Image (cartoon, grey):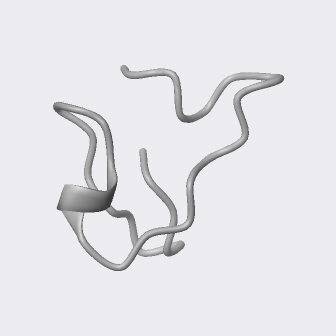
Amino acid sequence: GCPQGRGDWAPTSCSQDSDCLAGCVCGPNGFCG
């Protein structure tokens, strides 16, 4: 998947999928992934 969940790639806080990279969604954790 996209680099929003790797060791040194902590996720991005989001409220919608548009806050995230392409193909990534805003998860229930409130973070991109």
Name which quarter of the figure residue 9 lies in. top right
Q: Position of residue 7 (x, y in %)?
A: 81, 23
In the rendering, at what x and y percent does residue 20 appear?
A: 32, 48
| 23 is higher (above) or lower (below) than 32 | above
> In the figure, is residue 19 to the left or right of 12?
left
Q: Is 26 situated above or below 7?
A: below
Rendered-image quadrant of the C terminus: top left
Pick the front one: 28 or 16: 16
Instruction: State how many labels appear.
Output: 0
Q: Is residue 29 left or right of residue 9?
A: left
Q: Residue furthest right?
A: 8
Q: Residue at x 25, y 72 (%)?
A: 16
Q: Position of residue 5 (x, y in %)?
A: 60, 33
**Which residue does the image show at 19% across and 58% down from the upper left?**
18
Residue at left offset 53%, top offset 34%: 4
Residue at (39%, 22%) from the top-left corner? Answer: 2
Say which quadrant the N terminus sits in.
top left
- Taking 31 as reference, is 8 above or below it? above
For residue 17, which quarter of the picture?
Answer: bottom left
Q: Where residue 31 sits in the image (x, y, percent)? A: 51, 63
In this rendering, is residue 9 above or below 16? above
Most extreme residue toward the front, as rendered? 19
